[PDB]
Image 1 (cartoon, each protein chain N blue to C red):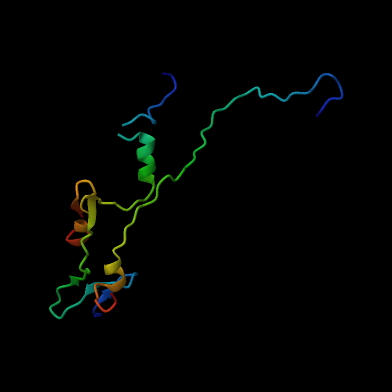
Image 2: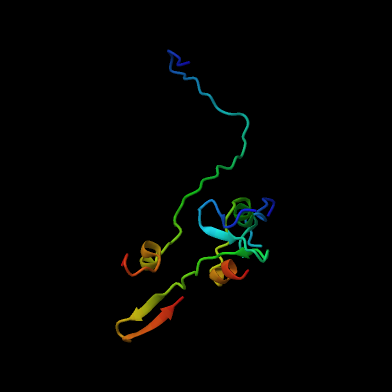
Length: 48
Length: 41
Length: 48
């Protein structure tokens, strides 16, 4: 509660604790290269 | 010193680092011979 | 009793024969090819 006076109320902790916050950042992705000739035509000349 | 950093110490990956990889389920990349492992093996 | 066996992908991974020796069918896997080339050398290295 704010005080209507020169003095002001302060809320200050009398106890302390340590806790760990875990964060994950994704800096990389799996790198994939596709062989189009085998995948699209299944090695068939007519498709090519 | 009194603070324990053994978990963060390299065992080289650290213990927490190795534990995270073990907990996550990842298919073996097999970069050296993966195609051979899929075939005869 | 049933003949050819298929996986969830519907690829033909199995076959049944009159001899009774089970055969697992694996499609002829392609061998990956990549080119490592340096313009100054004007030479290339095949990569698998």
